[PDB]
Each structure stands twice: as C-alpha cells, then as structure tokens.
Image (tube, coloured by chain):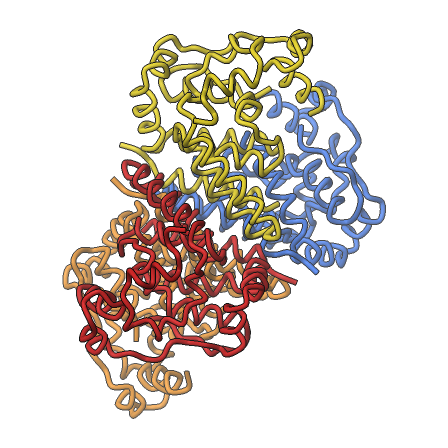
Chain colours: A red, B yellow, C orange, D blue
C-alpha cells in the first residue's frame, strides 16, 4: 500500500544534491516522504495525543502576522525575540486535503518558532540539535532523515566538527526527552505576547 | 588530500544494496571510508588516548583461539559466553601496512566480543545499539555510517519498530557516555578467563 | 584537477529526482557537469572544428527576437515554423566567464531551434532522438548523460515504449552522423528568414 | 505487479560501486532486474521469434565441454578459437524455475561465446560494443543498463576514450541491426566443430 523505495530514492537525491536554493531541497524531500509508511504512522501516533488530535480535527494553522508588529511587543516575549532575529536573517504552501498534507502545513507554519523556545541556533548544528529535540518528543519522517543526513554530511565533509555535532544531537535528544509539553501541540499564534522563559516553564523544558 | 565524495558514493551504494552476503557488504563499505578525512581523524584522536596509542605502536592483535577450548572455561567467563552463543549462531583479512589498516584489523578481530561486555543482542537493533555505545566512547567512520543507515532503513522499511530502535540507540549512547574504560583499549585475548560482570566492573559500565 | 565523482553524484541525483519544475532539474545537472574532465575535453574538441572555434572567438550569442515578428515571416522560413510551434507550446541565464560557461549559454540560447532543422518532435522521444543527433555531430557531457538517462528511465518505467525510444535514438545518431554541417556552428539569428528545407540542404542533412 | 524502483536502486548501486570481485557485481545487478517490468517484456518479445521460442520450450542449455578437447579441434572452428583465447585469459549458477531464470542461465552459459562470432575484443570497449550488437538484435534489461553504465563511466572517468567507446557502440549496433540470425537463438554446443567464418555466414553478419 506504501512506496518506501521512493523514500530511499528521495534520501539518496537529498544526500547527492547537498554535495554540490537550499530551502526548496528540503520541501521536495518532505513531499517525497508522504508516500511512505512512516508518514501515516507519524499521523496515527500524533492523533493518539489528545491536544494534537484536536488541532487535526480543527485544521489549526497560525494566524498571519506582521514582523514589524511582533517586534513592537515587550523585551523577552516570543514575538520580539522571533522578529529581532528574522530582521537579522516564507515557505512552500500546499492545499490541506488530508491528515498528511495538514501535518506538513502545521510543521512548515510553525517549525521556525521551535528553535527560539527549545534554545538552538539558526546555524547547521543548531538545526540538527533541534531535530533531535523534536524526534525525542514526537517522531516524524523528516526529523529522522535530517538527523541521519546531518551525521553523514558532517562526518564526510567537515569531520573536525563531528564532536560539536554530537554534542548538539545528544543535548537536543536529552532535553526533548525531558520536556512533557510537546512543541507540535502548541497554538503558537496565542503565545507571541508571552515571555520565552514562561513558555519554556509551561512546556517544562527542565522536567 | 582526501576523497570524501567517494565516501558518500560508498554510503549510497550501501543504502541501495541493502534495499534488495550481508557480512561482505559492510567490509566493502568500511574499505571505501579509508580514503576519507574522518578515517585519518579517528586514528589521530584514538592515538591521543595512551593505552590505545600503545596498541598502535605494538600492532596488537588478539591471539588465535579454538571455540571448543573457550567453551570449556568457567560459567560466567568471557570465553564461555562468547563460545556458547557462537555455536548457537570469520572475517575479511587485510595486510597491516599503516595506522588505518591496523585500526581496521583491530576492529574486525575484536568487535564481535564488544556486544557481550556492552550487553546488546546479536539482532539488528542490538547491533545499532552497540554502534551508539561505541560512537559515545571512541567515534570511528563505520559507527557513524551504520547509525544513520540503521535509522533510515528502519524508518523507511519497518517503521513500526522505530520506537524500539530509538530505545536501543539512546540506551547505547547513554551507557557508552558513562563508561570511562574504552572497549577499543582492551587486550581481549587476556580477558577470556575473566567473568563478564568483572570486565563490566573494570570498564566501569555503570559510572 | 577535476571532480568527476561530483558528476556521478549529479547523475544519481538526476535519476532519483526523475523517479518521483522539470526544466530547472536539467539546468542544475548541466551545471554540476562543468567541474568534470569531459566538460573541458568537449570544449577542447569543439574548438578543433574551425566554424565552431569562430563562435568561441566571438563568444557569439543570438540577437533578441520578438516571437510575433518571427511569425510574420514567409511560410516555410525558420522564424515562422519556430514561432508557430512556440505559440502552440525562457531559460536559466549565467554570466559568460570562460569557454565552459560560454558553451552552456550557446547551447541554452539555441538548442530549442535544433529540433525544427533536425526534424524531431517536442515530446520526450523527440528530445532523446535530438540528443542522439547532437552526440553524433558534436559530443558534450549533457547529451551523453541525457541519452543514458533516457534509455534507463524508459526501460525501467515505461518499457512498452523502449522499441520506439531505440527507433528515435538510432535514427537521430544515423542522420546526425551523415550531417557534415554542425548545428552548434550556425549563427541561427541570421537564418530566421531562410526556408527550413534550404537550411537542411545547406547543412547537408541527407549526405 | 513489478518493483521498478528497486531496478533504479540496483543501477545506482552498480554505478557507485564501479567508482571505487568485478564479475559478481554484474550478477547481483542482473538479479535485481528480474523484479522489473522490462524483465518480463524481454521474455514476452523473445518468445515472439520462433527459433528463440523453441529454446524457451526445451529450456535448452549447452552441454558440458572440456577446454582441452575443444582446443584439439581444427584451426578455424568455434571450439579451437574459444579454447585458445580461454587459455590466454565459470559463472553464478541459479535454479531454472521460470522463463526469467531460464533466460538468465541461457545468457550466462553462452554469452562468452558471442564475442568470437560477433568479432569484439575481451576488453571493456569490446564488451560494451558486444552489448550494443545484442541490444540491436534481441533487447534484454542488462544490455540497456550495461550500455548506459558504459557511456556514463567512460565519459565521467576516462573521457579521452569516449570517441573510441562511441566507435565500438555504433559499430556494434549497426552490425547487429544487419544480422538476421539471432545470437540468442543458436544451439552453440552443436557449432564447436563449425568454422567461425561459416557461423558468421549462416547468421548473415554482413546482410
């Protein structure tokens, strides 16, 4: 019923293209994983968590925001932190037709907020660190693929930075494993005016 | 000075062949990684640990053993445990010409003993668990490649067993990170007559 | 001095992506072949034919045209035929910095004219047939890659059309081998007002 | 009903391994193509030629021979020529269970004789030329794959020999297209005592 071999072909494509813009390569890969068994299983397991199943039922997606208005919010709030680093540094839209296309949209609309709450950098290691945190909480295909990819590309092309990469991966997974409050379960558009330290405390980043 | 692109080609070869005996596929892959920068770096970092550098200097390799004589040793000894499970279930030999060909031989001669001391099964998950333990202690290219491979092949082809795979990977890395006594640093041929619990205690598997 | 392994990675990327827009995939591939030895050798061999070496000296590229003005030319002329089928059915620009970036631009600016003079369809088989005609005359890396790709993708995914593909490939090569007048050597912008039958006669398509 | 994606994975495996014994790599690849649609279609099309369909009915395979006894035959006979060059320079056996396993065995048992009758060298280019002759007569998946592979590996890794490769490929295809007597249709074990010139005349190599 599922074409997993096309998932492997998509991963081989991803590894090979990266050995030669960069934002669209991940979207093309993500799309190729929709046909796999892990795509359906991820949806089946997320729908087992009540607050996540509610978002699937509602088809919840964050309200549009103006970066300039977010920047005008208090000093340590989610809005201010996100906007300040967006100006210092938006995705491929798909029609929501089923559970898989919904999860894809929920992920794309919200995942760039994750690293600010989780406490990871916008750099390569920070992004691999964040994936390890997500995988520890709620495993989805792209997170598994991006972790393996990360490990392979750093050890092959920049092995002098492998220890650093493993330090972020282990920290990410460890912290994510001890965070009961799932990132994916949050209605982010309602947290722009809330302190980042307060959000971390609500999710129980320490715990 | 290093051909890393051939390392990526070797990994793509490995992923693709596995999607179709199995022992020789890993040896061919291992050999293809000798040309990479990570191969040299692994040697450079291992030689920084005194007891490991001594084995490189000596060109230490384990003495030949007769499985029947090992089985005749006491109940809980390394020899007895290894032999009992070998009979219930030997590799590609290369001439030792340099540091990389030495490490390859040391690895091949001894790595099948590792899982009995580390406490991992001979199955697929047990082997991926063991790699995570080794990577936590002394990172070498094959261990990184086999971890990524594991993660990708299970999530693509048997995703219903991904949680189980992550459970072994995390346990492996966690235990390995808390084991000061390096597996690679041991003169295994001198431990056949020593209790497994005693070896685990010497290496400080708990710590 | 050349990275050929990256050429193989580009081909693997191309095959794998083509097993899942389509115009940019060929450009990305073409670009990845610039680093190979065949890229330089193709330039070295083309520069051995005087008429071609003349365009390399001038860094000749076709003058801009308005499709509506070309359509207004007499019945059987190159301009009229091209425009009529363009309306019934433009590329990635690169700065001309050397002979490889030059040949890439010459190819992209002019190759869509080739099929009208050569007599091949705009469809998949017509394009693979045209590449066979081009490889018979003046071999360049993309033609070789596009031919192999063609053969592999049809035999793997649509084998019921393999006989038809081999009919276009052999016709293309045969006709191209018997055409002394090289396509690549022509200053196309000077032939818009010339009959297609006259151009075919000048190039000696029969011969 | 067929897994074509596994055929593509097998080709990617083959290309990548060939960028680093060599006899078994082709057999593993050949085996991976049995699951494709082209495998069945090749059998369906071969069984449409009566002389071939006769061998499919008998599941004909050549009788065993002693190389020393073949060498003792007259000067220009098939036996003598084959044996003389075998001594100057045998395969993976599979149980014949269906038409695909049959064609695989017929191919492996007899294909080394082909080059002596067809007039191609035992070298790399001679083998690629022979496959072109075979594809012109009776197309089977391995020939298509071996042709594409050939073209890609020479243009990527030894482009200075591409002209020579295209000379053998076009000669092979041209000669094969003009040979009515199919190689695959011959009961070779009955021709050991027949002159090579006589066999070429019977098959109509010129025609």
Left or right of residue A188: residue D123: right
Residue at the bottom extreme of this rendering: C72
Quarter of the rendering occupied by the N terminus of chain C: top left
Quarter of the rendering occupied by the C terminus of chain C: bottom left
Give the x, y percent position of residue A81: 23, 65
Q: Is residue D132 visible?
A: no
Give the x, y percent position of residue A83: 22, 69
Left or right of residue C126: residue D85: right
Place residue B185 in its image quadrant: top left
Q: Is residue D112 visible?
A: yes
- Residue located at (31% from left, 47% from top): C36
Left or right of residue C134: residue D100: right
Residue at the right extreme of this rendering: D58
Which residue is nearer to you in this view: A113 or D149? A113
In the image, is residue D196 above or below residue A192? above
Left or right of residue D61: residue C48: left
In the image, is residue B54 above or below residue C66? above
In the image, is residue B106 above or below residue C125? above
Give the x, y percent position of residue A145: 45, 52
Place residue D189 in its image quadrant: top right
- Residue located at (80% from left, 44% from top): D97
Which residue is nearer to you in this view: D150 or A155? A155
Give the x, y percent position of residue C102: 21, 60
Which residue is nearer to you in this view: C140 or C178? C140
- Residue located at (61% from left, 39% from top): D28
- Residue located at (31% from left, 25% from top): B45
């Amino acid at each position: 019923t599922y074409n997993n071999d096309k998932g492997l072909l998509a991963y081989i494509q991803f590894l090979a293209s990266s050995a030669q813009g960069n934002t669209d390569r991940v979207f093309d890969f993500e799309d190729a994983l929709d046909q796999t068994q892990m795509a359906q299983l991820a949806v089946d397991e997320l729908k087992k968590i009540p607050e996540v199943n509610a978002l699937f039922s509602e088809r919840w997606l964050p309200a549009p925001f103006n970066l300039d208005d977010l920047a005008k919010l208090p000093e340590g709030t989610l809005g201010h932190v996100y906007a300040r680093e967006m100006k210092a540094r938006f995705y491929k839209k798909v029609p929501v037709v089923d559970d898989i296309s919904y999860l894809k949209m929920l992920w794309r609309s919200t995942h760039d907020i994750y690293h600010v709450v989780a406490g990871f950098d916008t750099n390569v290691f920070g992004e691999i660190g964040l994936q390890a945190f997500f995988l520890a909480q709620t495993p989805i295909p792209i997170s598994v693929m991006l972790l393996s990819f990360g490990m392979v590309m750093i050890s092959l092309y920049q092995p002098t930075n492998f220890k650093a990469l493993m330090t972020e991966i282990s920290r990410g997974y460890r912290v994510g494993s001890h965070t009961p409050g799932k990132l994916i379960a949050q209605k982010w558009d309602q947290l722009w005016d809330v302190q980042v330290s307060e959000i971390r405390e609500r999710l129980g980043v320490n715990s």
